[PDB]
Image (cartoon, coloured by chain):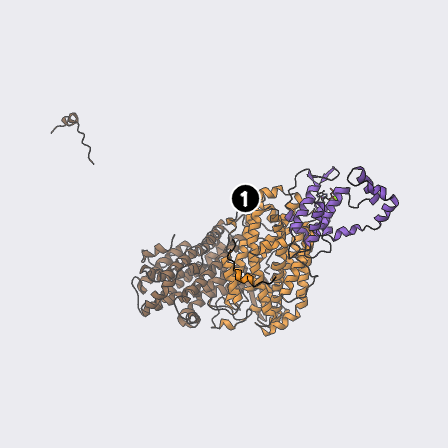
Chain colours: A orange, B brown, C purple
Amino acid sequence: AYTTFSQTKNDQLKEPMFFGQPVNVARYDQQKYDIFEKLIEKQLSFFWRPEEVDVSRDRIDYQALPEHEKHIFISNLKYQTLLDSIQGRSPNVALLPLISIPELETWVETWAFSETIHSRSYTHIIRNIVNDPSVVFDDIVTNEQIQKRAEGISSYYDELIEMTSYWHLLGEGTHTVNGKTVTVSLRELKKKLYLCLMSVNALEAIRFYVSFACSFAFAERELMEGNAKIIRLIARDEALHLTGTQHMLNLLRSGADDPEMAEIAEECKQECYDLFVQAAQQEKDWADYLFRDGSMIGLNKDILCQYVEYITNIRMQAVGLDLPFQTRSNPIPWINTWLVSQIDSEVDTDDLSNFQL
Amino acid sequence: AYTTFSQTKNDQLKEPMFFGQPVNVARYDQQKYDIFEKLIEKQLSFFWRPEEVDVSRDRIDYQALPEHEKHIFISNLKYQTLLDSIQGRSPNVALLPLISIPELETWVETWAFSETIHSRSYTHIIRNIVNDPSVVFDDIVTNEQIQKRAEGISSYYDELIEMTSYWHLLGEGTHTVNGKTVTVSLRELKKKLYLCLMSVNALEAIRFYVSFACSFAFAERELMEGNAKIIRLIARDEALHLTGTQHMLNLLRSGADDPEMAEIAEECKQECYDLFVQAAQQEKDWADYLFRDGSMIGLNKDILCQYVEYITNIRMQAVGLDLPFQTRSNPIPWINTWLVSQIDSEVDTDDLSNFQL
Amino acid sequence: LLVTKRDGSTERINLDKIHRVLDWAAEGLHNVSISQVELRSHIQFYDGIKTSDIHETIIKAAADLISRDAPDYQYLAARLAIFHLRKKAYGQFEPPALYDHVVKMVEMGKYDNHLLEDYTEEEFKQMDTFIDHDRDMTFSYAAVKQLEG
Ligand SMILES: Nc1ncnc2c1ncn2[C@H]1C[C@H](O)[C@@H](COP(=O)(O)OP(=O)(O)O)O1
Ligand SMILES: [Mg+2]
C-alpha cells in the first residue's frame, strides 16, 4: 500500500522515476536526473503573483472590442481557466502516489503549485475585464465546445488514478471484487502512466500554445496589455512544464529508467500518435468555433490552424513520434517575442619609391 | 470514483469542505470560508528562498561547538528534515482527493508547496555546515531514535489514504474483496480524516515548535545565526499552517460545515485527547535523546519538557480539548522574539496676605 | 464603421478583404506571414478611412519585413505595390488596351503625339500581343518603388 514515509532505507539514486519505493527523506544535495532539480530552481526563480501586474487599463480595451472579438477573448480565457484547473490538482493526485525519487516528487508539487498561480491570475484577469465574473465561471463546466475536451483530458488522469488505487490496495494479480473478477497488471499501470504523460504533454505543449497565440495577438495590437503580461509569465512557466514531461517521456521511452518501459512505450506508439493527432484536430475545430462570427487583425481560422500544424510537428518530434502534418514555417513569427527572453598622415617616400609605374 | 474535473455544474459555495463533489473549476472570486483565501494570500507574500540567506558563519560556529552540542543541533535538524519530508507530500496525497471547495484545495497545495521550500532549506543548512551531507541524510532513515515517530505521524496519513482509495473504488457499503469482507463506511472515513487533521495539528503546533526552541536557543547565544534566520522564516510559515488546521478542525467540530461531522467529532473527543497527549509525551521522549550527552545554556531536558506542556495546553485549548497538564507560565519567554513579526518668578503678595498663619 | 473605397463609395469594414489580398500576394512564397504583415501595419481604423491609405500602410509593413531569414518578402511587397499601382493608373487590376491607353495619354499631353503618327491602330494592337503583363510579377520591391517614384 502507499505510505507517506516508507520505513525501508533505499538508495534514492538507484530507484526508478515511477513505481519504485515511495520517497521517504526529501533531500536535494543529489539527483538521479538533474533536469528536475534545474526545473525546480528555474520555477522558483520565476515566482510571480498576479496582483503585481497592472491590468486596470484592460477593461477599457475589452469594452471597445467588437462583439465577436469579445467572444474570441473570453472563449480563450474560459478554455485556459479549464485547463489550468485540471493542471492545478491533477499532477499532485495522479503522480505523487507513483513517484519514487525525491527530485521528481518535489518538481511535481512545484509544477502543481505554479498552476494554482495560473488559476489565480485567470480570476485576476476576469475580475478586471468583465462586470460579473460569475457569468464566465459558470459557463466553463457546461460549455459544449469546452466540455468535450475537458472529459477527454481528465479521463487519462482519472484512469491512471483508478488503476493506481487498485495497485496500492490489491497489488498485482487476479482479484475478486464483489463477484466480478479484477486483474491488476503493473504493465497496464505503466501503460496508463505513459499515455497520461503523453496527453499532458499535448495539453501543455500544443493546447495552451494555441491559446497563447490568441492572447498575444491582441497584445500585438497594443490591446489587453495587462492580460498579455500575465500570459507572458504563464508562457514562461509553461515552457518549463512541457520540458518536464518531455524528459519524463523520453526517459521512459529510452528504457534508461525501466527496461520493461522501453518495450511498453513502443506498444503505445500508435495510440500516442493518435492521441496527439486527435489533440491537434480538436484545437483546429476550436479555432473554427472561435472565428465563426469573424476574425481580427493578425489571426483567423487559417492562420491559427496553420499554427496548430506547425506547433504539433515540433512537439511530436520532441517525444519521438512521426510527424502528422506537412513541413511548414512559423505562420505567426511575432509570437516568439512573447515566449523567450582621423587619418594617419605619416608617409614614407622611400616605401613609395619602390613603386614602378 | 475520483474525477479530476467533475462534469456536474455545482454551487461551490454550498459544498462542504470535504467529501462533497470533487472540485472542478478553480475560481478565487468567491469563497465559502475566506480564512483559506487569506492564508493563501499570506503564504504567497511570505515567499522566501533559502539561498538568499547568509549561512557562511554557521560552518565555523558548528565546528566550534562542543560535541554534545553538535548532537543537539544536528539531531534537531534531522528531526525537522523528517517532519517536513512527510509534510511535503502528505497534505497533497491525503487531502486533495477529498476536498470539495476550491479555496481549500488551493490552500492545501500552497501549504504543501511551502513545505518543499522547508525541505530544501534543511539541505541548504546541512550542506553548509558538514562535509558530507550523505552522512546526515542516511542517518535519518537508519537511526532508530528518529524513525520511531515517523510511524506515529505517517500512520494517520496512511490509513486515511487507504480508506479514501476503497471509498473511491467501491463506494459506501459492505463489499467482499478476495473472499475477505470489507466494509466502506463514510462515517468511518470522516472519522479518519478528523483524526488525521488532529495529528497534523499536533505535529505543526507542538512538535515543530519544540524544535524551534532548540534552534533559537543557539541564536540567543549569537551562535548558528544563519540557521536561525532560516528557522525564523520557517516558523512564520508554520504559524499559517497550524492556523489552517485549527480552522478546519473547529469548522468540522462545530457542525457549521457538515452536521454529521459534529457528531463524529464528539465520538473522537477522547481519541483526539489521547492523540495530543501522546504527541506531547513523544516530544518529551525526544528531548531525553537530545540531552543524553549534556545540555547547554538556557536549555535542558527539564526546561524543554516544561515548554512541551506549556505549548500543548495552548494548542489543545484552541481546538476545544481538555488541558492535560498543570497550568504554568512560559518557561522560555525569550522565544516570543522569534515567533512573530524651570521656575516662574512671579509672586502675588495680595494672594499671600489672604493666608492665616 | 465604414471605409472609403477608391470610387468614393463607402461600405462597412471587412478584414477578409485584407486577408484575401495578402493571401494572393503571399502565394507560393516561403517563410512569409499574412499575420505578421497585418500586425506590423499598426493600422489605426477611423470611420471613413480611405481604402488606398490602408493598402499603402500594409505595403510599407511587408516591405520592412525584408530580411535574411525571410527574403521572399521582397516579392510579397512588390506584388502588393504592383496591385496598388494598377489601381492608381487604371482604377482596376487589368490594364487597358495599348491603343486606348496611348490615345488617352496623348490627348492629356503626357505622351508624345508622334506615337499616333508613326504607328497605326492595327500596329498598336499588334504590339499589345507582345506585352506580357505577368512580367510585373517578377519585380522585387525595390524595383517597384523606383518605378513609381
Ligand atoms: N471593406 C473593407 N475593409 C477593410 N479593408 C478593405 C475593404 N475593402 C478593401 N479593403 C482593402 C483591400 C485592399 O488591400 C485595399 C485596397 O484594395 P482595392 O481592391 O484597390 O480597394 P477597393 O476594393 O476599395 O477598390 O483595401
Ligand atoms: Mg477591392
Examine the image and state in which quarter residue A285 appears. bottom right
**Does the beta carbon at disc 1 come under 8 Å from ligand 1?**
no
Judge by depth and name the residue closer to the eye, C99 or C11: C99
**Furthest residue toward right:** C122
Residue A333 screen position, x and y as percent: 63, 55
Q: State the residue position of label 1.
A: A56
Judge by depth and name the residue closer to the eye, B175 or B128: B128
Judge by depth and name the residue closer to the eye, A169 or A212: A212
All told, the count of numbered labels is: 1
Which residue is located at x 73 percent, y 56 percent? Answer: C28
Image side of residue A198 versus residue B45, left or right: right
Residue A86 visible, this orientation: yes
Q: Secondary structure at mark 1?
A: loop
Residue B28 screen position, x and y as percent: 54, 50
Which residue is located at x 40 percent, y 63 percent? Answer: B279
Letter of the chain that mark 1 sits on in the rendering: A
Examine the image and state in which quarter residue A238 appears. bottom right
Disc 1 marks a residue whose amino acid type is Ser
When the figure is inspected, residue B247 is found, relative to residue B143, above or below; the finding is: above
Residue C1 screen position, x and y as percent: 68, 39
Q: Alpha-carbon neighbours of circle 1 within 10 Å: few (<14), some, or many (≥20)?
A: some
**Furthest residue toward left:** B357
Judge by depth and name the residue closer to the eye, A180 or A67: A67
Which residue is located at x 64 percent, y 62 percent? Answer: A314
Residue A182 screen position, x and y as percent: 63, 69
When the figure is inspected, residue C4 is found, relative to residue A121, above or below; the finding is: above
Residue B15 visible, this orientation: no
Q: Look at the image and tell me in which quarter the C terminus of chain A lies.
A: bottom right
